[PDB]
Image (cartoon, coloured by chain):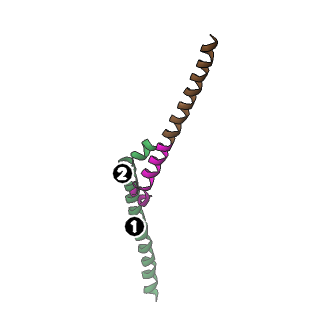
Chain colours: A brown, B green
Amino acid sequence: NFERERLKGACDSTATAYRKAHHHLLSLYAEHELEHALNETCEALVRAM
Amino acid sequence: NFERERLKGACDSTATAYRKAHHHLLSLYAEHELEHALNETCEALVRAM
């Protein structure tokens, strides 16, 4: 049981780290995509407005 | 001069009528264009946001 406790602790730690890294990468991709979609296309909307 | 007076009155009248009609046409066109340009295109921005 003592050996299992620290292993479960490390498991939770690495799970949290993986979650954080995943969220960070997804955020980077979403930001780049929104910027590139707002700067390049959707221009007739500007002249219409 | 009395004949010129009513002429200038009718001149201002037809001028303001033409101006109103032009503004109305331009407004209708701009509204239709904005609606048709927002409803159809600019959809990738929605998924980006």
For this orientation, the residue located farthest to the bottom is B1
Secondary structure beneath dot 1 equals helix
For this orientation, the residue located farthest to the front is A3
Q: A19 or B37, which is in the foreground?
A: A19
Q: Position of residue B10 (x, y in %)?
A: 42, 77
Q: Nearer the viewer, mark 2 or mark 1?
A: 2
Sequence-first tag of 2 and 1: 1
Q: CA distance from mark 2 to mark 1?
A: 21 Å
Query: What is the chain identity of the residue bearing mark 1?
Result: B
The stretch drawn in magenta includes residue B4: no
Label 2 in the same subunit as label 1: yes
Secondary structure beneath dot 2 equals helix
B12 to A8, vertically: above or below: below
Pointer 2 residue: B36
Q: Position of residue B7 (x, y in %)?
A: 42, 81
- First to last magenta residue range: A28-49
Count up the numbered dots.
2
For badge 1, the amino acid type reads His
Q: B21 or A30, which is in the foreground?
A: A30
Pointer 1 residue: B22
Q: B42 or A14, which is in the foreground?
A: A14
